Each structure stands twice: as structure tokens, then as C-alpha cells.
Length: 67
Ligand SMILES: [Zn+2]
Image (cartoon, rainbow, N blue to C red; front, side, top):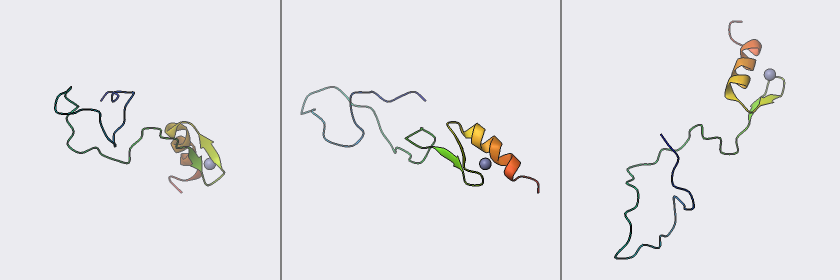
């Protein structure tokens, strides 16, 4: 939980030499999650797209579910 420190980057080169501040402890950063990274949920059935997953997900229920 929580947001990573801003004004920086995940991949690249750091300005820390022999001496400096201790950077965050990282094991393995997972990829492929709901972080709204310029992703829009669009409905292929009727072209219904919304800024929310619930909106689209709920919408699709009408298109398909128990038919
Ligand atoms: Zn739709």
C-alpha cells in the first residue's frame, strides 16, 4: 500500500556514490495491475466505455451473464 516516492524513477541510474542515503528495499516489483496507467475500459458489445471498472463491468452484466 501507499505511493512510491515521487521526483524519481524505478529504472535508471542514481546519483548515490560510495556514501549517500539508503534507497527503498525492493524484492520484486509485480507488473500488470489496476493502477490506471492511461488505460480505458471499453465495451466491445455496444462500444460502452467508462472511467470506472465497476461501470463497465456492471454494464457488461446486461450484455452477458446468465443467458
Ligand atoms: Zn456495452
